[PDB]
Amino acid sequence: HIKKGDNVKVIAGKDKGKEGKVIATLPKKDRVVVEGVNIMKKHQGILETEAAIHVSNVQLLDPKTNEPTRVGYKFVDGKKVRIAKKSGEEI
RNA sequence: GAGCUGUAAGUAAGCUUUGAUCCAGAGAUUUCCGAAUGGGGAAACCCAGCAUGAGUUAUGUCAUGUUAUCGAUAUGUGAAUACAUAGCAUAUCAGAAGGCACACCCGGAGAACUGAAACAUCUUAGUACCCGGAGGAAGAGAAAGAAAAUUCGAUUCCCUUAGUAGCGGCGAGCGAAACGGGAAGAGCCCAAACCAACGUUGGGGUUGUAGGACACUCUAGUUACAAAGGACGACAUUAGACGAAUCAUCUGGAAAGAUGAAUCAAAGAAGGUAAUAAUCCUGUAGUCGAAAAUGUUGUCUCUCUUGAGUGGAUCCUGAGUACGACGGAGCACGUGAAAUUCCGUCGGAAUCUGGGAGGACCAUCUCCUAAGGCUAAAUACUCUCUAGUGACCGAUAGUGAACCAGUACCGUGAGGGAAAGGUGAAAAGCACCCCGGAAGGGGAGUGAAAUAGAACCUGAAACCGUGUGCUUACAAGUAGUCAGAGCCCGUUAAUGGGUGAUGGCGUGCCUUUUGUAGAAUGAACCGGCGAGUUACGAUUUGAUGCAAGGUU
RNA sequence: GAGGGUAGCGGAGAAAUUCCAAUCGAACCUGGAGAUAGCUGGUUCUCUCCGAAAUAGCUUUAGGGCUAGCCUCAAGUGAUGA
RNA sequence: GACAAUGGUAGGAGAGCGUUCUAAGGGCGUUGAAGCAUGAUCGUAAGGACAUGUGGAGCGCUUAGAAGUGAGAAUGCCGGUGUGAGUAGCGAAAGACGGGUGAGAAUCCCGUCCACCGAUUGACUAAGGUUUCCAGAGGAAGGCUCGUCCGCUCUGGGUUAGUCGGGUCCUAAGCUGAGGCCGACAGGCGUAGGCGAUGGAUAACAGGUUGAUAUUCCUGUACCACCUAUAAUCGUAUCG
RNA sequence: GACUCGGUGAAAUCAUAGUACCUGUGAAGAUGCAGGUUACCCGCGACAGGACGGAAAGACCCCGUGGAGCUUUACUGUAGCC
């Protein structure tokens, strides 16, 4: 659904409306780490680190107008491509 | 199509768009024990022969293959004993052996407690157990039949006939069938007479509205029975792919909730997501896809293939069988007037002008043709698969087992057998300071909440403690009830709440008994669990529809 | 002392109903099996109306059962009750 | 608005309360559901509301339907916790003192006296057990008290054979046996042949050494079986 | 051993208990009922009369149309033998 290094928007949670770059992925549990989201404080001094959120809480913005949208698959070329729902432009 | 190195957090060293892991169909490798099979043996071990190979100056050692016992088939196959029909040796073999599914099927063998209010005939019962065959089913099956109609026409299963006929120390109890309505539905091959070959099957032929041999007119079938061995196109099964439609505001640690305005539907089945989502995620409706491997089939291929036979004198069918007597068993039917069907022992028929049956037996009539074999479909059952369903369970429940359970543990052994689920949305699992040898604890910090800190959701009663308002050391108490001063409080607001100087009355509860304070029985206390239910028949009452008719 | 043999409708016994894995007048385990019990014990919420018997006959019967007699609920026939 | 009825066991009849689930309709809940705790509330009974604290996600109402639908007794089953009660007991026996260790010593370590066994409580070895053996480090639980200690916990170690005891040697009892005999089925007997010590045969001794092994390792001297090459009898042997 | 101190620390039993005596009464032998008499609250060491004291659904006795073992000229069968 969301690949590593793509740009997404937080749709739900405590940081709703925060653009970031995915920098990690956990497909086994469906969780993804997005930079600047879910910062947590650990005890071991206090080392602040970023927690992983649910993959169903982030959306990909349109390339042209930066609008959160769903991903489609036209599959014209021999390799399938990700197509933005709002506009056919590839995401 | 970007991540990966099982459960599992870490600590490491590494692989991967040259496309890793992961999923599916085919191949390779596969130690030792175990039918275990080279010989032994206390299974998972020990000890050998033969052949061919490396190693070693040689011996010791090592590696890869072969050697169990019984069957059916070659070869030699000279003992008592001069045919020889003992043994005895080698060769060949998708020949056997053992193991499951508390389940279904056929056969062998075969109890008891119990009921009859005792008990032996009888019943429970041809049931349990044991053994031995199998097969995806088995078994049965092409009339020596059912009957009495102006007849039907292989077997099996369901409804009905019916709790009827009948059986029975005629007690207790047991218990049919044929007609009629349905599911399914095809039937064939041998022996014999005879015709050709030197106890191989070569032809010929298969039966009752009588057949064949023998004399006589004369141009389709398929390996699921009916004889059996292959070549040839299309659908499904075992990984997948695409797949419509939402944005704000308020309360929150968090929106899917509330408040407004928009949307998709051949998709409003469901499961997740920091709370209750048709439009956030995985899916659903619908529509596509198969290297290679299985199964079901369709086509031509392949094999195999002569049918009506008018006469009718002579010939043919299945024997120690059919049947009888004696002793048993089986048919709903206990020897009874017991027909029909079987086993052991003896005696023993007929031959188409024959033989058998129609509930003893005879006559007449009617219907069939035994003593050889094979045969699919309608039926029974469920280890274990792939989809699903529930006015079923929700941790003392549900399988003994929601946890690594037939495991802790118990027994020499065969066997018996438990207890144990829940932090949070996210480990964000309390850095640091202080008391202490530690354990533990008080602060700080994380979080929405730490009376959520892993002996971790909620946290009832028994039971054990601390503080306090009233009360008690002259008193005889199933401990309560009615009457009633003083002292301390102030509620769901009303003829209020707590404590109790003193007076009247009063010998627990259950079970069982003519009768219990009873010294008759039962309970240490608290919690959970724990006993007239269901399926087929009969009868009566209420309700309801129709009515000389009602209902399948 | 070591290694062996005899098993329950059975073994062993210089004999006691003595022993066969800590209870043997007939061992242990699983199954038929929820054997049978005319005998004991137990059997869970609340109100309203009515309300007994402990007798007769028969009984392989006497602490069991059956019919009759006394209770209750309905539908009926009418002074037939005291 | 009138008169008349209402004690009750075994039993008969009638009307109701509450619990779980289901179908329709209509409603509450993070502005806090169920459950739990408390109170001076309502109805003829079984029972029904309301407020507050705790709790943190489900649950009432109306009519009808369907039941694993109501607990104080069964010497009832399972779990938890009392009473007796700070009561009985703490499993044959001689100990004392001075040092050491340590948070903590009648109980651990070292030393000196004393006491007990000595056909033995001493020294070796079969069966059986199966790491209980050694060293350093530990004190939650186990040890009938204590514990710094341990047959307890953690980490790392320890068993050396041609000759000792068993296999490539033999056999008793007994147990299994190709063919074979006998039996409803299984399977019961049994010959040749095999298996089977508690017995027969059979080549090593004395010292030394480790925290833990010794006829095994080491030092010094032996013996048995089997291989290889080279020399003695100048064979009509030799092996069976 | 018991008894007094330090350490450790069970069991049978148990309807709730603020648990006196005498004469009488009662299902006929009362801590609990009637009438009298006596008794300030709470411990420790001892004795054993009674709570029909506590361990075992009384083995004696009688009942069940209940079991099991044994005996015989009880009934009906049977191995075996002639």
Image (tube, coloured by chain):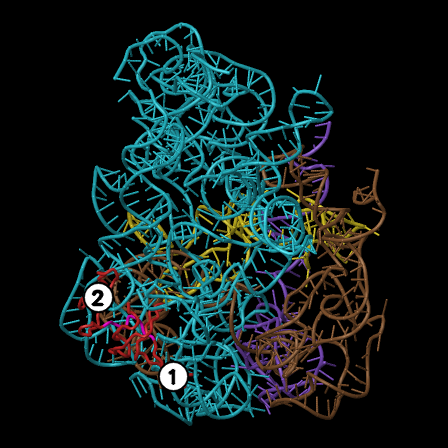
Chain colours: A red, B cyan, C yellow, D brown, E purple
The residue drawn where x is 23% and y is 64% is A72
Q: Mark 1 belongs to which subunit?
A: A
> What residue did someone put label 2 on?
A83
The secondary structure type at the circle numbered 1 is: strand
Residues B31 and D9: in front is B31
- Answer yes or no: are tags 1 and 2 on the same subunit: yes
- Relative to A13, is B177 above or below? above
Give the mark nearer the N terminus: 1 vs 2: 1
Q: Position of residue B221 (x, y in %)?
A: 32, 28
Q: Is residue A58 magenta?
A: yes
> What residue did someone put label 1 on?
A47
Q: Mark 2 belongs to which subunit?
A: A
The secondary structure type at the circle numbered 2 is: strand
- Relative to D233, is B84 above or below? above
> Which quarter of the figure has residue D211?
bottom right
Report the magenta residues as a range.
A52-60
Residues B139 and B247: in front is B247
- The N terminus of chain A sits in image quarter: bottom left
Residues B102 and A90: in front is A90
The residue drawn where x is 30% and y is 78% is A35
Label 1 or label 2, whichever lies nearer to me, is 2
Q: Position of residue B298 (x, y in %)?
A: 28, 37
Residue B12 in the figure: left or right of residue B244:
right
Give the residue type at disc 1. Leu
- Relative to B112, is B369 above or below? above
